[PDB]
Structure formats: C-alpha cells, structure tokens
Length: 59
Image (cartoon, rainbow, N blue to C red; front, side, top):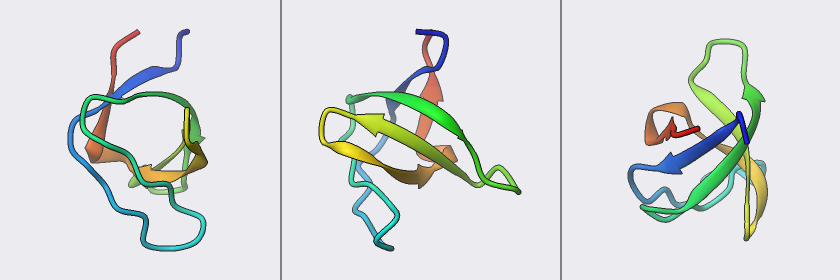
C-alpha cells in the first residue's frame, strides 16, 4: 500500500477520536490534520488519530 506506515513508539489513546498503537505495528494512513501534527490511521484494532511523529512511512 502506498500509505503503509510503521509505529515507532507506543501511543495510548487520549481523545476519543485517537487510536492506541503499539511499537512495531503496521498502519494505513488516510491523511493528516491541518498542521500535520496528527495522522488518521487504520490498524487491525480500528481507526483513529495518532501523532504524526510516532509513525513513519515504510511503503
């Protein structure tokens, strides 16, 4: 997938619109928020926003 990313660090969901992720997990990114600080991502656990600096593309 062109939008494949990997989690660099664990992230515990904060807001209801965020998604917990674990270091090493693969994600598909749907997009970014207005300032690029958050990414909307899909994992095997669901969908939600994660910090953009906690993930990086690996396509």
